[PDB]
Amino acid sequence: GAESHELQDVLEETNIPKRLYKALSLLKKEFELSKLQQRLGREVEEKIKQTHRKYLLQEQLK
Amino acid sequence: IIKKELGLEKDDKDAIEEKFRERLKELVVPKHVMDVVDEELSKLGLLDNHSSEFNVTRNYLD
Image (cartoon, rainbow over all chains, first blue to last red; front, side, top):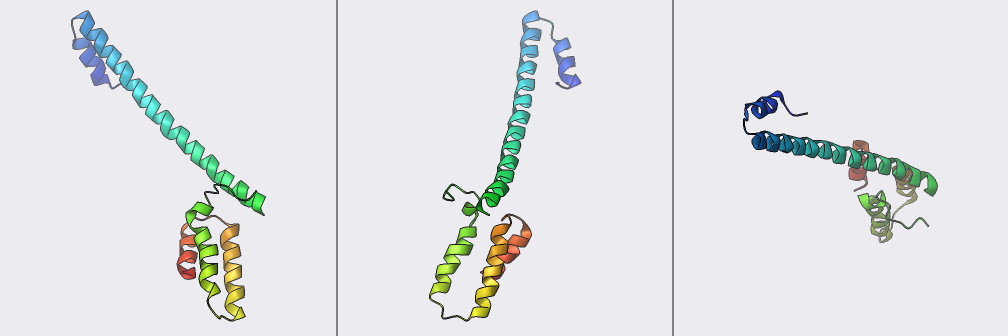
């Protein structure tokens, strides 16, 4: 999911090792972005479920 | 069984219920405020803690 500028920079690379290493770096960057999004989400669902559980515990107390 | 982590209890609402109760203990105080505070505390406990109206209730109780 990297920006088109990254693709242009990869194309500009001539040596095969350079292009492959830059592609690997872009893969790692996309992996990091996806993992950050997944972590932020997962914690958000965890805490919203904990809020619904707060209400559930209030009902149990009632 | 009520005794748990009770994140709701961790939000000072116990300091609105028990701490204020003990503060009121040493107060030779009439019954009108007794019923008023009991009703307000029941409303506070029956509901959540975070929202702004609960901050208003907390300041009023303080």
